[PDB]
Image 1: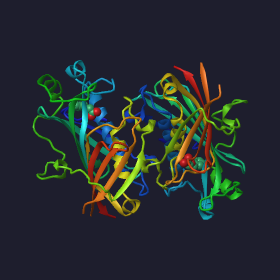
Image 2: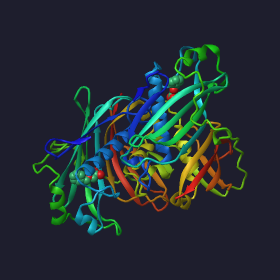
Image 3: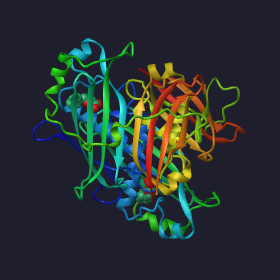
Length: 269
Length: 268
Ligand SMILES: O=C(O)COCc1ccccc1
Ligand SMILES: O=C(O)COCc1ccccc1
């Protein structure tokens, strides 16, 4: 991959692998999500961020601050097939003191058409106490030089689905998958559960018949709390709606503490 | 990737990704195993095999026969770091009417040194009845033209660890991880559990302290039966010794064996 001419965005091409695809021979939403995080990491490396484990500026490292994902929004129009080349362009934007945003645009390398788009909201947090905090001027000045100053949105639209408030699913759930546990392959280089694993867990409670007859077009996921390596998760889903919509909830198996809430929109194959 | 000059082997380069590494910032053995299967798939595509879902010759497709993994053996000397380029060379060989073998050699693209090697034994089977069959002459003649005829071994050595008989672990196990279930990400394009998931399950019963202080040098795994999408697995491990372990995966309820294996770890 490489930074674009102005050094304000980053592009990378990927060839879809045999184990990265589902029954339709096209990349799963989890493969897409992994590719988005990889291109984000390569963008941080290309602009001087160290390979320490967490992308931090000088002030962030000094104050033990890290960026953490609070919400992820992905919309796919066409999933790349096994062997196809997908091109991903990514960039970051300061959201004042609230936090920061990373956006992505997915394209078919052969036709040049937009096949998907994504956006993620990051909030600043102390690594040790897990307490959120506003972005300081010292931190903002340090990373602002790597961002476009004028607004550049992947989801420009006025009443778009990336800014909708997600309600908490009420018991009883229509569908559920219980006893979900992370294995070592679900952990990242920092021994934390990878954000993409939560997407997989959310999708585990969607009945197989919906998966076999529909394509996932939109997924919105809020991250409230982390699943530790020794935690067990219950995945809950209720249909809210040729389109099917679902409301999702991940919670700890025992006490029922919420870890994630989300929504999915599927269209008929 | 591309076939080599003689068209009898295939090479491909991979850049190690951020999510593909463990806490040492080097590729996990599961990432390596995924890369080996990917380069195997690209080799089958480059020699005329269709993208149907199972690599089959004309007579295999007619008789509903598929190759299935019976044994996988991987030895790693150095794991590639995040951002490093690993080069993998792969080839197949006829093992008479017993089956087929796929071998791999892993190299550091920058230094050119061998950083790992792997071998897998495949057996032919009817995809519907699940019954193993010997390799017929019609099938042999069809794929022999894509293999070196003289022996070419990734593990040539006599008395090497890739041909050792693995015993069945006896209860009680020293360590265990119970209630393991596959999710949709563990399935392949044919809706079967990916072979690499079994490697992950085997490793789940290795205590974390061994993982934190040792590096996995060798893993030998036998595949006896598949775990279905609605099955639950128990992973069992006992130290037999460098640290050596004997492994067993079995169905959570009836205790039917799905895999047995061994691992050898080196002190960091
Ligand atoms: O996406 C990540 O993993 C980290 O990106 C940090 C960054 C990169 C470029 C510009 C601002 C911030
Ligand atoms: O590794 C696979 O997935 C299938 O490879 C089949 C093959 C490829 C080349 C030569 C003989 C057989």
